[PDB]
Length: 152
Length: 53
Image (cartoon, rainbow over all chains, first blue to last red):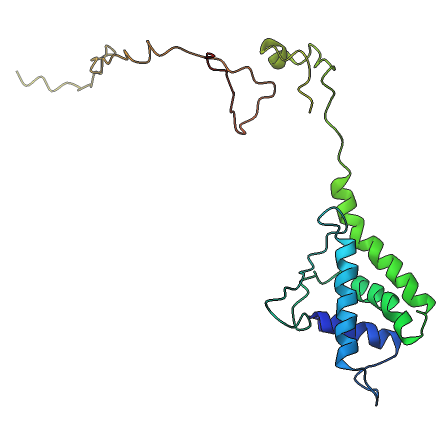
């Protein structure tokens, strides 16, 4: 993948919006780029709700290493499109824009695909209640006096 | 004599006992059976209480 930093994600988002690309004769300011990186950090932090949200592998920058741009985002290869399409949707209003229908649809699809595997992982069944017997067909448990399920 | 008959080999099936060992400590170490629900090779930690003070 040719998108390997937070600024790379931001550049992909701007190109997707059609504001700035490698072919355009006019470009956006580095301050606007840093603002877009702040937006990206905020969006990913709101997704990853301290571990109880969308798990992606994103790495949050620290103040010790100064530029958040330039840091590898750490996403797997299949989260980049979702991340930068959602980023384009989020940062469109700054430039008096409105993301096109295709961008919005790809953002929805990408976010759902991002959360699919985590949803499958969290679809877990609870253990038996503490008041449920283990039956008598469980000869080992009933010989060891496990007449009722442990629970918890 | 020169009785050049036909030679055999005979292996008798009485054994020569050689090993006779005793196990005194294992006959004094008391045996326990753990009350575990499922039969798993996973960590078999059974917790038992200690006399109160």
